[PDB]
Figure 1 (cartoon, helix red, strand yellow):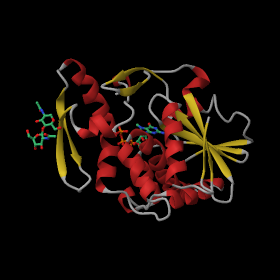
Figure 2 (figure 1 turned 135 degrees about the vertical axis):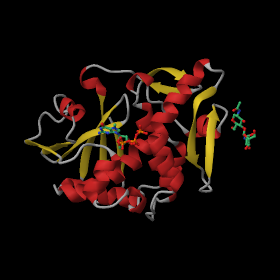
Figure 3 (figure 1 turned 180 degrees about the horizontal axis):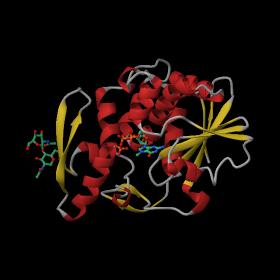
Figure 4 (figure 1 turned 120 degrees about the vertical axis):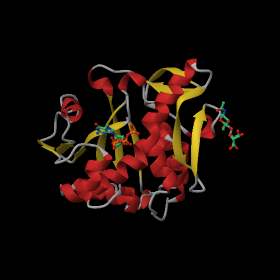
Amino acid sequence: DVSFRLSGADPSSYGMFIKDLRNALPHTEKVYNIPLLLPSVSGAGRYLLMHLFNYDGNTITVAVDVTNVYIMGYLALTTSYFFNEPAADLASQYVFRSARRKITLPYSGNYERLQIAAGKPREKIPIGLPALDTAISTLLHYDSTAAAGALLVLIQTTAEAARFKYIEQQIQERAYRDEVPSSATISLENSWSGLSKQIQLAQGNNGVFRTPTVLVDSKGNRVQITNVTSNVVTSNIQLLLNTKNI
Ligand SMILES: C[n+]1cn([C@@H]2O[C@H](COP(=O)(O)OP(=O)(O)OP(=O)(O)O)[C@@H](O)[C@H]2O)c2nc(N)[nH]c(=O)c21
Ligand SMILES: *[C@@H]1O[C@H](CO)[C@@H](O[C@@H]2O[C@H](CO)[C@@H](O)[C@H](O)[C@H]2NC(C)=O)[C@H](O)[C@H]1NC(C)=O
């Protein structure tokens, strides 16, 4: 398991958490020096449990699929909650078995669905460590509307930070003050699958992407990523989604 405590949290302890999260995702191979998540994992080993504690020390446990860093559901006291998708219902067979009741959320785990349920795109939703404390608090008591926004915060401050060093740094900058994600943050989130696939297809194309990936950079400018010498590949991305799962 991995854990993160918002009480006493600073850029450094958040960093350790993101490192611990990445370290808990298995790989047998690295591709252009980037860990390649597994094609699949059988049984309960498929799910990582993240123990998150808010400022007051209350806690939720979040179930994460180690092949794709997708959050499947979470446990709040004696109730488990799962996204309304076959993958999460499959996860429910393995995690939080001991919960008193299991609630299926009235949405699946994707950004579009969650933004509809929350009432705002994530461009407008502040993220940061304080926002993560708010999200943990919100998830402790069922409210499907509030939970959508909380889960949008949670996914970004965990899974997305694990996937991109830039995103991890963005959250570290927001350790004491939330701010809506940069356009580069949104762009990277949106391109993870695409990037993961082009990096793998470059393996036998001399490091050249079969298809250029369009991104917004740190200055908020639109750049074209065409090969593995790009800083997005050499410095930023930390985990690759396996092409088997694309
Ligand atoms: C398809 N899918 C993706 N995710 C993750 O939840 C977030 C919202 O899901 P998404 O499908 O909107 O992701 P996105 O468009 O960013 O696609 P990607 O670049 O290929 O990852 C994603 O960004 C992933 O973090 C998903 N999470 C869950 N729980 N279930 C899913 O079916 C699922
Ligand atoms: C490989 O990617 C690099 C970028 O990392 C490309 O070089 C960039 O492209 C043009 C000049 O050709 C400039 O706009 C950028 O400043 C360049 N970046 C750097 C870091 O030099 C390069 O063209 C790509 N190679 C191929 C074959 O597509």
